[PDB]
Image 1 (cartoon, helix red, strand yellow):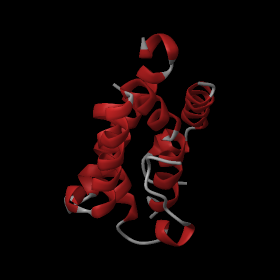
Image 2: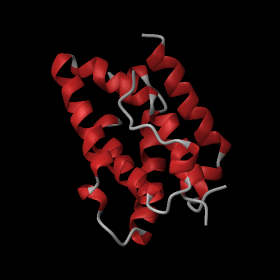
Image 3: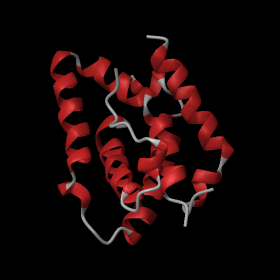
Image 4: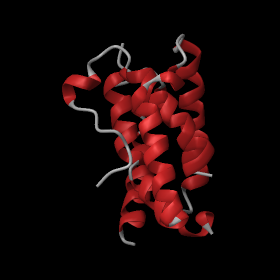
Length: 136
């Protein structure tokens, strides 16, 4: 499972899969979390901070291409808000969060639309990281 209940909603998973399939019908931006890494205590809040960035930047035409992106973002915002309430430490100062931001910006310079689509396709993977690392 996970703690935030939408992470246990198969409807959200489907929407994210849908998003991925679309984006990819057009290397990685997300930092890679191994199985061992996801078991580490900070992993939940680290990915939650990345989720925050996703809600603000990545999942912000896009409505036309991704009819579900609005509902996904709102759902993801709810998850982020609950996680942030229990994430005592501010992980903006963590290397992996900066990495994403750094790599996303580096990609955005080339092509903003391609960078957005790429990160969008990786949202499903981020959800998986949250699912595993945010279990009590």
